[PDB]
Length: 573
Ligand SMILES: O=[N+]([O-])c1ccc(OP(=O)(O)O)cc1
Image 1 (tube, rainbow, N blue to C red):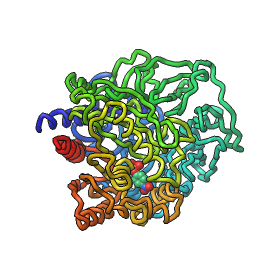
Image 2 (image 1 turned 30 degrees about the vertical axis):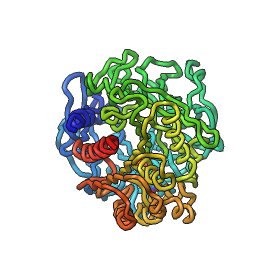
Image 3 (image 1 turned 120 degrees about the horizontal axis):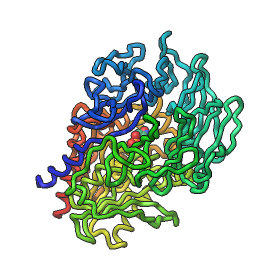
Image 4 (image 1 turned 30 degrees about the horizontal axis):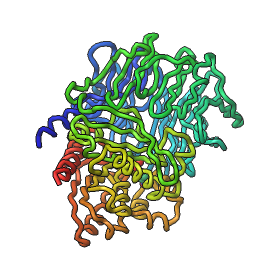
């Protein structure tokens, strides 16, 4: 029913912005989705300025005012074999490939103006690199996913998922390399930034709260940072999205709890629109950050006014399809409380058609943040339930690590409960499961382990077999999988939908990017083979020249359109 396409394509098309830093003297560096693809722009108060030629994937963090931007573009048609390109800001649209770096999964990076420090992954290692005038140097080989946080002088700070789901903090030297890894018996570090005193300020997420610590690298000492203003310290945040020093020394922090964040400057809370904020930068004296919300696509506003600098306005009608939204606390199987964001659709009755949309990750969370899938779903006439199952971020360390070694176990029990809640609360008249990635893994775990729960399910870029996916993984994922599963082949086998297909009883729609190197297509072709033989009902959509990263309005459409079509079809019985 085309009345569906009109809105879904519109929600997809709305320009989306993310903030990166201040470059070229004093212009904001931003990444926005606009024109039908992901590009990098300079903004200076008026018209925006495209920096790259063809679509990119992202930009490396630039120090304040540097005169160049390092683009990160996939040169593998989706497989995510990134190549790094340099662009001088005075000469927009001219790129010089950094041929010193061979294509790899570029995980993160910063550009000091003189040196380029990033972390990449290959079939054999995740490493911390540095590319300056003398060429490429590997500063350290890392255990698993590691991301660069900040560079001040020779001191490099980063975050690393080096074991058991915990995030550790590491330091290295830009000229002499090396690696130090600081662990915190109390939890995981969520952000880092180097202080003028050359100590590492970091967010620390413990079982309960999230606190500000100072970590002296010279040894490893940790102590609570004391801020000038006490506002911050009296809010008790659950997580710290990002923190960092502005040019003038003031400490900027973005803390969050229950799905919404606040921004503090030296401990003094600055007013910011409700929702969630990205990094904070000092621009011409003023404070800029990125704002988002279930009803507001990622935009860039001024603080404290909230006035928008760059923003893809969301239309009135489409804005009107989200009748409301709540944060609920679904009662799980073990007595656990699953924070769940719900979205009543203005186009469905109550009770009515509901979709338990499962977030990916698993270390992610459903928060007060723009979500294209849930929005279009509301648009198509379905209420949306988004449960922060155990393994989610944003609710403490204890809740986040409960998934380690237990995939397709407890979190799945939390997803089922969200359904149980949707039905018993009066919101649902019928139930569907839909998700991309770990979310799509969950659809597959729900349909197999728990037939009868949902009327049908949509699994996009889904996990299908830990064993095979493993042997097809680069150093970052293989390690990441070794962490989720605990490494036991009993878990990898027993917690793989591919092995319990006989149990399926509902209609399945498989959507998968042909070149996805995060969740490979190969196992999904075996699944389809299994579905066929067992005489199971299913439809599938494999997408051309695309990977896990959806960075063009055509791939987003090819991925969301089939989904909404599938569900609208099941809804009419
Ligand atoms: O291999 N893995 O363990 C694995 C691969 C892809 C995943 O999905 P993502 O979280 O959305 O990047 C999650 C886990």
